[PDB]
Image (cartoon, rainbow, N blue to C red):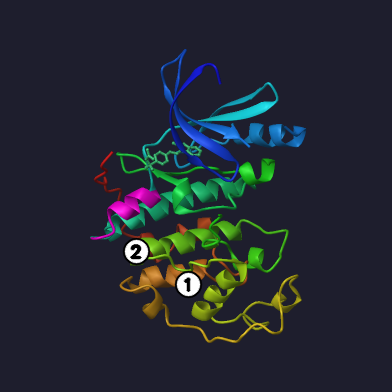
């Protein structure tokens, strides 16, 4: 903490405050994260350091000093939330949405193959650079260690404590929809509002569509029954390839919901390219 000249506070996270900081000895600009320490956690984090991929924001150093923890990460200039806001009036071009989504699925497919889950994907954890790359931040901190419930998967909301990599697919599906319509898909303001927002669009799940759902911890027989809506009405004007992919990412049953690896082979990515965005830094 003495070797860093904190420039600005980049924002608070689920596990701590992040600062844009400049390393004194090296001059390099990094993202320093002060974790808000157990032995398990240290080991957890230390595995994440060796998890390298072009679509994962790199964990550079871990500093446990004076019984405090700080994580040093590579720095990217803008998050997807700010870029979306900037493009609110015109929307993000489909060719760019398609490239960002393809890159994110590659990152997830890498993490998921190493049994690492993000568990808290949101536009704010997605970082972009001038070269057209997009990277995931916070990967693996959930395991080792007002909040937005907008991108939370149904199984978490219903009390499943042993969730899987499918939760990340769901969150990504929610971000995919938001980039296309320029409006949050399920903006719930509490857990039950969140749940009901999902039920009102996708229909209240039952044993036909989701076997075992009625035996979930927080499922109540008293849940109102809503019918399912046409996706054509939910995500206009996404073409049929996009909508079919989206429906596979938003399946209720985690076991049925598409994997990141299978998603990469979907017809929607037949014409992917890597356009370079216009970023105002
Ligand atoms: N607020 C500013 N300055 N611009 S911005 O809002 O687009 C913005 C700019 C940079 C970042 N970067 C965040 C991060 C970064 O670079 N690496 C990380 C690793 C872990 C957690 C967060 C980060 C996040 C937001």
Marks 2 and 1 sit apart, C-alpha to C-alpha, by: 18 Å
> Which callout, 2 or 1, points at the residue further toward the start of the chain?
2
Secondary element at image label 2? loop
In contact (CB < 8 Å): disc 2 and disc 1? no
Identify which residue is drawn at 49% across, 47% down. Answer: 107
Say left or right for 79 vs 149: left
The label shown at residue 247 is 1
Along the line of sight, the residue nearer the viewer: 242 or 181? 181
Per the picture, the main secondary structure of the magenta-coloured stretch is helix
Quadrant of the frame with the C terminus = top left
**In the image, residue 140 above or below residue 67:** below
| Mark 2 neighbour class, 10 Å CA radius: few under 14, some 14 to 19, many 20 or more | some
Along the line of sight, the residue nearer the viewer: 274 or 214? 214
Say if disc 2 is inside 8 Å of ligand 1.
no
Between tags 2 and 1, which lies in front?
Answer: 2
Q: Position of residue 147 (x, y in %)?
A: 56, 55
**Ligand 1: which quarter?**
top left
According to the picture, the residue beneath numbered tag 2 turns out to be 182
The image shows a total of numbered marks equal to 2
Identify which residue is drawn at 34% across, 54% down. Answer: 84
The reply to whether the magenta stretch includes residue 127 is: no
Along the line of sight, the residue nearer the viewer: 261 or 49? 49
The label shown at residue 120 is none
Identify which residue is drawn at 49% across, 38% down. Answer: 53
Bounds of the magenta span?
Answer: 80-89
Quadrant of residue 54 within the rendered picture:
top left
Q: Position of residue 8 (x, y in %)?
A: 42, 31
Q: Position of residue 223 (x, y in %)?
A: 65, 82
């Amino acid at each position: 903490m003495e070797n860093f000249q904190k420039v600005e506070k980049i924002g608070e996270g689920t596990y701590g405050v992040v600062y844009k900081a400049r390393n004194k000895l090296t001059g390099e600009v990094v993202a320093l994260k002060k974790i808000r320490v157990p032995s398990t956690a240290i080991r957890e984090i230390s595995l994440l350091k060796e998890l390298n991929h072009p679509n994962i924001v790199k964990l550079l150093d871990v500093i446990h000093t004076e019984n405090k923890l700080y994580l040093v990460f590579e720095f990217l200039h803008q998050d997807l939330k700010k870029f979306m806001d900037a493009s609110a009036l015109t929307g993000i071009p489909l060719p760019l949405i398609k490239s960002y989504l393809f890159q994110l699925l590659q990152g997830l497919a890498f993490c998921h193959s190493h049994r690492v889950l993000h568990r808290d994907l949101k536009p704010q954890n997605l970082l972009i650079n001038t070269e057209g790359a997009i990277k995931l931040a916070d990967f693996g901190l959930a395991r080792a260690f007002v909040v937005t419930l907008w991108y939370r998967a149904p199984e978490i909301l219903l009390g499943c404590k042993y969730y899987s990599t499918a939760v990340d697919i769901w969150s990504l599906g929610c971000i995919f929809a938001e980039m296309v319509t320029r409006r949050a898909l399920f903006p719930g303001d509490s857990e039950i509002d969140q749940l009901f927002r999902i039920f009102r669009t996708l229909g209240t799940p039952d044993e036909v569509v989701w076997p075992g759902v009625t035996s979930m911890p927080d499922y109540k027989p008293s849940f109102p029954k809503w019918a399912r809506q046409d996706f054509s009405k939910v995500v206009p004007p996404l073409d049929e390839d996009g909508r079919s992919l989206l429906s596979q990412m938003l399946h209720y049953d985690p076991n049925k919901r598409i994997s990141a690896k299978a998603a990469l082979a979907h017809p929607f990515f037949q014409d992917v390219t890597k356009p370079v965005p216009h970023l105002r830094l």
